[PDB]
Each structure stands twice: as structure tokens, then as C-alpha cells.
Image (cartoon, rainbow, N blue to C red):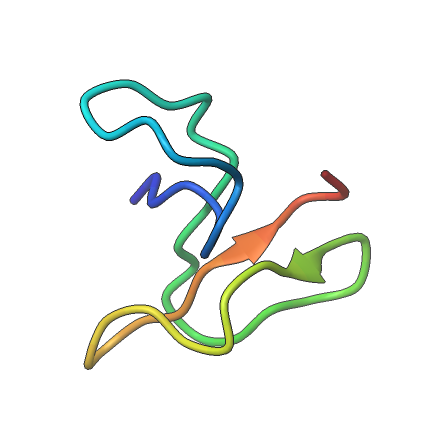
Length: 48
């Protein structure tokens, strides 16, 4: 579920979708972009 980074920039209607939601937990090769995300999911950033 693309969610962009917790703060990759301003914008609002557009975005480079620099956020990825993985049901479970972040894994190696990734970089948490948001301390959290949804009530049932997070949001990591596959290496920038």
C-alpha cells in the first residue's frame, strides 16, 4: 500500500510514492520512513 515517506516533501495531490506498507514488519534492505503509519500497518522506505 504505497504511503509515501513520513515526510519526503510538501506537495499534497502528487508524490513519488517513496513509502511502502508491508503487512508484518520492516525488513533488511529497507529504511523506516515513518515511526508508524496506519493502525494496522507501518511504512518503510526501500533504501530511499
